[PDB]
């Protein structure tokens, strides 16, 4: 599923992401935009052989098990395919573990390079949340 901007904002808020660990909703919507373009089915392979999954492009090396990443840790206890669902709950739950990880949202390279320090409030502008 390809979410609309405000639709995703509302789904994320409902599942408790707004200000989770100090990160406003605009941060999460911005990250989804640049990581997957709001598409739950997005997958991208990495150079080390691991693969990024879903709306938040969660990496198979540490977070999920895709059965093809030798030595993956699967810290979120889920098959990576679960992250491609039209229901963002699993992705959000795993993201909550990642952001609590100590590095914050810097774990997401697109957030660091394209969202960090920008007026992320523009991302939820006009939405009825």
Image: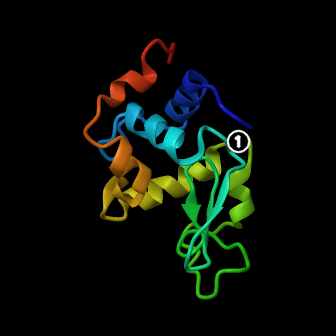
Query: Which quadrant of the figure contains the N terminus?
Result: top right
Please state the horizontal and vertical placement of residue 46, each as a whole percent of the image: 58, 70
Secondary structure at numbered mark 1 = loop
| Residue 100 quadrant | bottom left
- Please determine whether, in this image, residue 95 is positioned above or below residue 79: above
Q: Is residue 17 visible?
A: no
Please state the horizontal and vertical placement of residue 107, each as a whole percent of the image: 39, 60
- Please determine whether, in this image, residue 6 is positioned above or below residue 63: above
Residue most extreme to the front: 47
Please state the horizontal and vertical placement of residue 41, each as a whole percent of the image: 72, 49
Give the left or right position of residue 37, taking residue 105 as reference: right
Give the left or right position of residue 51, taking residue 62 as reference: right
Residue at image position (42%, 16%) is: 125
Give the left or right position of residue 89, taking residue 94 as reference: right
**Residue at the disc numbered 1:** 87
| Residue 26 quadrant | top left
Residue at image position (50%, 43%) is: 34
- Please determine whether, in this image, residue 64 is positioned above or below residue 118: below
């Amino acid at each position: 599923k390809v979410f609309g901007r405000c639709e995703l904002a509302a789904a994320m808020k409902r599942v408790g992401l707004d200000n989770y660990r100090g990160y406003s909703l605009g941060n999460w919507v911005c990250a989804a935009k640049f990581e997957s373009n709001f598409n739950t089915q997005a997958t991208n392979r990495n150079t080390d052989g691991s693969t990024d999954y879903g709306i938040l492009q969660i990496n198979s090396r540490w977070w999920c098990n895709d059965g093809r990443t030798p030595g993956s840790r699967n810290l979120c206890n889920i098959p990576c395919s679960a992250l491609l669902s039209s229901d963002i709950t699993a992705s959000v739950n795993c993201a909550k573990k990642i952001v609590s990880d100590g590095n914050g949202m810097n774990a997401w390279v697109a957030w660091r390079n394209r969202c960090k320090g920008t007026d992320v409030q523009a991302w939820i502008r006009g939405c009825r949340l």
